[PDB]
Length: 49
Length: 50
Ligand SMILES: *[C@@H]1O[C@H](CO)[C@@H](O)[C@H](O)[C@H]1NC(C)=O
Ligand SMILES: *[C@@H]1O[C@H](CO)[C@@H](O)[C@H](O)[C@H]1NC(C)=O
Image 1 (spheres, each protein chain N blue to C red):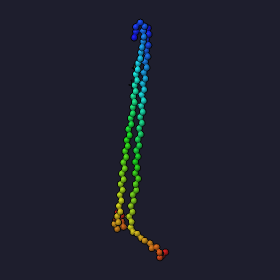
Image 2: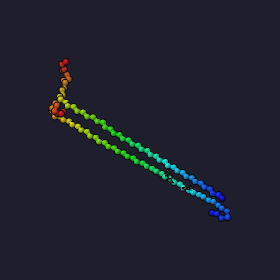
Image 3: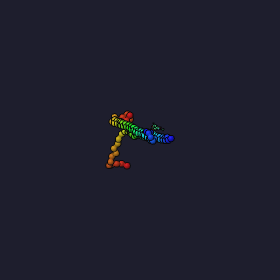
Image 4: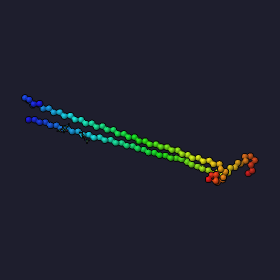
């Protein structure tokens, strides 16, 4: 009498996950204002001190 | 099969494969430029600037 038995089982599970995110914002500005009143022109020559 | 003498035979085969791929890309951009200029030669010391 003879009876042989064999059993083999394999099991594999791999998982990979990757995520990347980037956000950027920039704001640079300038404002200016001048309220002028009056202008003068100094005489160049024949000047008193 | 078995006749005058006995003969034994056994075979088994099983294979399984599973592949996976996932990709996602997102991008967003916005730009706005607003400039205001005002020149007034009114003729008032204060009110022209005001
Ligand atoms: C024979 O192989 C199958 C897969 O091919 C398996 O499911 C079963 O368990 C195996 N038999 C024994 C007794 O392990
Ligand atoms: C093992 O392999 C079987 C294929 O027969 C599959 O269904 C099962 O999900 C696998 N086990 C794992 C933990 O993934």
